[PDB]
Image (cartoon, rainbow over all chains, first blue to last red; front, side, top):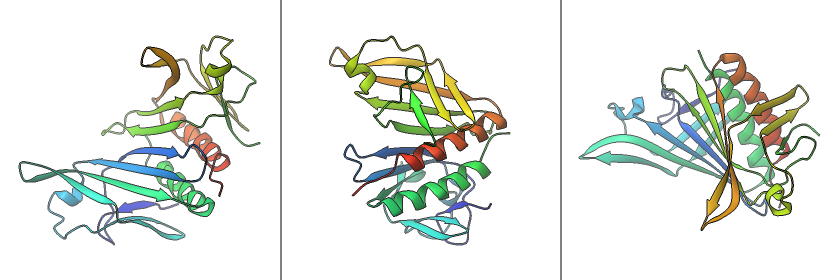
Length: 107
Length: 108
């Protein structure tokens, strides 16, 4: 059902990110990269962003590797990276992404 | 087995691609782009690749937009793009991608 991404807890981000998914050659680890073009939270959030929260029926998945991009003093974008080091983390993440991509589809 | 990717129909590709998923800002279209680093079909390198086939319990999803990718003058890799123009196409592709990613996961 409901799956969302939040930069501040309790606030769902409207902008849909580009998502890049990689898997290590030996199958030991994986990475999901999110790139947000002018996300609402930058439009004067106004609260400082300390993490990204992937929120669904199971709870949260959390990454602290999150960085705003600035041009001439203005945050214009956000990049986030989520690294998975175990089968359980990979499986948990795919479940979230499915719920997210399905409720974030085309018109 | 749930889902596989094929360059030649009937042969499952062993190399797992890097995958990039985009959505147009107005929600009108979406795109998935695939990067295969030296996929077996290139290493063994006999049959000519005319398409990429995404195969699962529901059937196949197909794209003809598939290209040899060169590194230092050598066709060592493949790029593919699958474009979705409708809600039906998006939802169906997400179903494949779930099954593929779930059966292509991590070891120890």
